Length: 193
Length: 180
Length: 14
Image 1 (cartoon, rainbow over the protein chains, first blue to last red):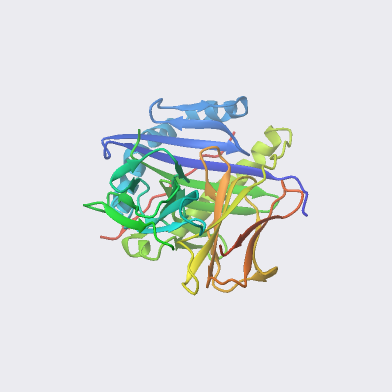
Image 2 (cartoon, each protein chain N blue to C red):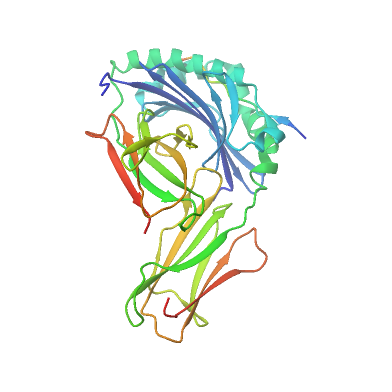
């Protein structure tokens, strides 16, 4: 309803961590709407205009030597410091997946179905989910949602298997995740339900 | 690649005079500062036991951002943001079973500017009881995303929609969900 | 045991 034009300024101060805290990169990034116009990169050591809109700021800010020294110390004073503060509840966080299996539509044997393995509530994102028919891994006919962020520090994923189920078959979904020491596995039997 | 990223994201939006300050770890929110209450709000209550943040510093950062926005608006010959309308998806927090408490999640993605109107509807009527939401989360393409939550008891009788308004949409976008 | 997140501060534009 409200059609007044909008104007947006964003600033993203980023810390990127490689190999624990052994390598850190700090990026101080300024945006006008969606477009980055100036940044400080710890791998460069000074501000650089990203668009011509940023040229005046880069020139102005690089002429202030105590500003620069402070940005140059951000890898330590800011990045490493904040990693330390949050590490116990972020880097160190692990939450178990919950696994459920169910057919997608209810229908007779010898007719095409999707078996769903739903994996829920886990943290961090890295997971692997495998389908077996009896004891052979099925890698054709696997339709997956990929990793879904729930926005509350958990993820889910749904990994579906295309089947034409026959009477005496067992299918198993197998989940591995850094919170688990041995695979979590759930079975589904080709019965009249 | 890189193990982890922490981002402190701020914005200021005119003429709405609305600002945000938040910290992000691998794409989840750690906390934000409420500009109304002027208070640090932890995404999970647990986080508050391990850490603190002086919400006043966020307020001061946003004043600089406001002042910069005035300058950049002028420097661009008053060129405004181009609306990018959201993608909306609705899913459940866990597999759906009758009478088992669950949560519908409205995931609103790839949009700007960071202003939306989001209503949960149950059978075509607005619902507020037990609902929650996040602030605007930053994306690497500099758009935003946002999540809304609705606790519910699944039934055969009910249908739900996530209703989303945004200036880049011609009409409000509804995304539907019902028990399979 | 309980630590304090530090904010980065934005610079003022030319």
